[PDB]
Amino acid sequence: MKELIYIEEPKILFAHGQKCTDARDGLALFGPLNNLYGIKSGVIGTKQGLK
Amino acid sequence: MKELIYIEEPKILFAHGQKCTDARDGLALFGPLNNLYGIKSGVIGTKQGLK
């Protein structure tokens, strides 16, 4: 037989120095790294498409 | 002796549809017309000058 070696799943850091393999799970529980006060979004498109 | 008329003071609109001749008083009581979630301020200068 021929050996296959497994690499440990990398961890991505989130807010408060917390680590988690999953991005969605870690982000939903610990939050993002920096504080964005708000997203002032600009919208361009059809008036029907704005709805 | 010559005539001298007076014009009514102009009013400026604030939040909640409220009007006030002054701006400092108008903001101090009613606030601005639109809401900015936050101001992300970037600073360029010396280390001493950032203090």
Image (cartoon, coloured by chain):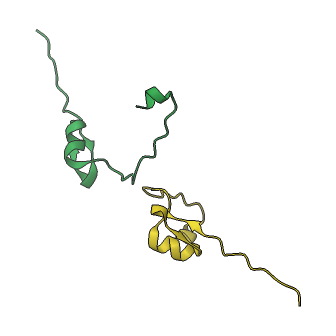
Chain colours: A yellow, B green
A11 and B27: which one is in front?
A11
Name which residue lies at 27% across and 51% down. B15
Q: On the rendered structure, is A31 left or right of B23?
A: right
Residue B11 appears in which quarter of the rendering? Answer: top left
Residue that sits furthest to the right in the current view? A1
> Which image quadrant is residue A49 in?
bottom right
Residue B12, how many percent across, how many down? 27, 41
- Which is nearer the eye, B51 or B42? B51
**In screen coordinates, is B32 left or right of B3?**
right
- Residue in view at x 66 percent, y 75 percent: A9
Nearer the observer, A13 or B6: A13
Q: Position of residue A2 (x, y in %)?
A: 88, 86
User: x and y percent of residue A19 in the render?
Assistant: 53, 69
B14 left or right of A12 in image? left
Q: Residue furthest bottom?
A: A1
Q: Is residue A45 above or below residue B30?
A: below
Q: Nearer the viewer, residue A5 or B5?
A: A5
* Residue for point 52% across, 32% down: B44
The outermost residue toward the left is B1
Q: Vertical placement of B11 versus B37: above or below?
A: above
Quadrant position of the C terminus of chain B in the picture: top left
Badge count = 0
